[PDB]
Amino acid sequence: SYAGDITPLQAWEMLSDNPRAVLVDVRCEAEWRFVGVPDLSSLGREVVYVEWATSDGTHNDNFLAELRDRIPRPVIFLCRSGNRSIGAAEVATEAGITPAYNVLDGFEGHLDAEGHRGATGWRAVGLPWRQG
Ligand SMILES: [Br-]
Ligand SMILES: [Br-]
Ligand SMILES: [Br-]
Ligand SMILES: [Br-]
Ligand SMILES: [Br-]
Ligand SMILES: [Br-]
Ligand SMILES: [Br-]
Ligand SMILES: [Br-]
Image (cartoon, rainbow, N blue to C red; front, top):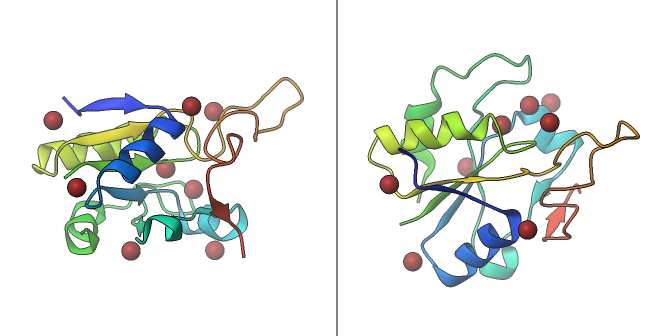
């Protein structure tokens, strides 16, 4: 039902090929603040921030209303590790905000053998990001 899963580099490529494509960071405010965020300044646009889950881990029941308010064709959804963003992509799709894509591996990726993230995901592949 949602348009597809794309890897972090594919997401960057899609944004770079489509001036009206939108990156929606759906992580909670605590992750934006303490972990960091993608940086689209080199593409002359802003990231759209709408929490899927709030920082207590529970769903933002105003997500759709906020999403429709805050966007800006392709709309690309980014979570911590690529999994909870599928729900956001499905909500976008059902709202006719399409094509809606999910970023595999997310911003931080999976927990590796040492109990560390930063192995896969947006930052691991060095796509533009900032935490100050
Ligand atoms: Br679609
Ligand atoms: Br990749
Ligand atoms: Br476009
Ligand atoms: Br979060
Ligand atoms: Br916070
Ligand atoms: Br925003
Ligand atoms: Br998320
Ligand atoms: Br994970």
